Amino acid sequence: PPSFDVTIAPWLIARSRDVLAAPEMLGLRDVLIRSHELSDVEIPLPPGAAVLWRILALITARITGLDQPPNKNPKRKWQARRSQILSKGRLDPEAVDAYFADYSERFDLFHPERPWLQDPRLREECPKTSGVNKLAWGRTAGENQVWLGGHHHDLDPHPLDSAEAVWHLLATLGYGPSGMCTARVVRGRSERNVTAGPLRGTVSYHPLGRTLFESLILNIPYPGTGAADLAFWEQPELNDPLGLPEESAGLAGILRLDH
DNA sequence: GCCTGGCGACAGCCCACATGGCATTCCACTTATCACTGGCTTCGTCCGCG
C-alpha cells in the first residue's frame, strides 16, 4: 500500500550551520530533532513555506508554547518559559516523539482514513477529479492556456513527486482559487462554488535567526488565554461540510489552521 | 638626370573731422466636445443549427 510520512520521508530541504554546501532533504521529525544543527529549512514555493512556517509553529512551538498562560501575568510567564527554552538552545527529542507518538499513525498523507490535511470521504462523492494540474501551482488548469511552465495539455499529465505533491497541497490549503471548483454532492448538496483561501494575496512575515530552533521559538504568536485549541490534523473526527466553522481562541485558530 | 637659379626699366611721402538728436498711447476672446473591449475559474443550461 502507498504510504508517505511527513515525519520520516524526505521532502524538507535543509541547510546546515557549517560548510553551506549540499543541502539534504529530510523529514519533518528529523528537522524537528536536529534544529540547532541546521540554519534553516527551505521550500521552493513561498505559499508552501507560508503555510509551512504556520504548521511548524504549531508543532515544535506548541510543545514549547504550552497552550496555557493562566494567571501569573500570562504574557509575562509565557515570556519566562520562552526565555527558559530559548536559553536551553534546543528541544529534547523525547518530547517530540511524544507529540508524534500521540498521532504517529495519523500523519502519512495517503491514509485510507484520516489523510494529512485532507478529507478521505471526498473520493467517493465527486465524479470528476480536479487533476494534479488543477491542484499544482505554475501548472495549467482546464481552461488555462498552454503557454507557460512547460505545456500541460491535460492529457497524460506527468505526476508530481510525492514530496512535490506535499508542497502544493499545503499551498492550495493556504492560497486557493475561489469560485467554480468541481462540485461534490453531500446528501443532495452540489455547489461548484468555492470561497478563497484565508491568506490569499498577502505577505506573511516570519522572523528568522541564526539557527532553526531560534526561529521556531520566535515564530509563535503569543496565544491569549482562551479555549484550548487543536489543529485540523488534531481534530478527533471530521467536521462535515454543513454547519458552522467553530471559533477557536487557541493559537490553532490564530494560525488559521482550525479548518 | 636632377636641381637650382633666373626671367630691361616699373617711384617716393604726407594726409584721414568735429556734434547733435534716437517717440508716444492703446488693445489681447468665446464654446462645445473628451469611446469602447479583453486578456478569472468549471460547469450547466439553453438555444440554435443540422
Image (cartoon, coloured by chain):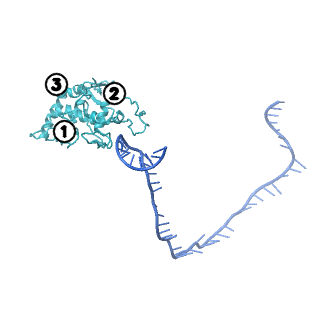
Chain colours: A cyan, B blue
Secondary structure beneath dot 3 equals helix
Q: Are marks 3 and 2 on the same chain?
A: yes
Q: Are marks 3 and 2 in contact (CB under 8 Å)?
A: no
| Residue A184 - label | none
| Residue A251 - label | 1
Percent coordinates x, y for residue A218 in the rendering? 21, 35
Question: What residue is pinned by disc 3?
Answer: A94
Between the residue at mark 2 and the residue at mark 1, the CA separation in whole angstroms equals 32 Å
A2 left or right, relative to A148? left
Q: Are marks 1 and 3 on the same chain?
A: yes
Q: Earlier in the sequence, mark 2 or mark 1?
A: 2
Q: Between residue A238 and residue A43, name the one nearer to us.
A: A238
Residue in the image at 32% along x and 30% along y: A165
Dot 1: within a 10 Å radius of its alpha carbon, few (fewer than 14), some, or many (20 or more) residues? many
Secondary structure beneath dot 2 equals loop
Secondary structure beneath dot 1 equals helix
Question: What residue is pinned by disc 2?
Answer: A161
Chain letter for mark 1: A
Chain letter for mark 3: A
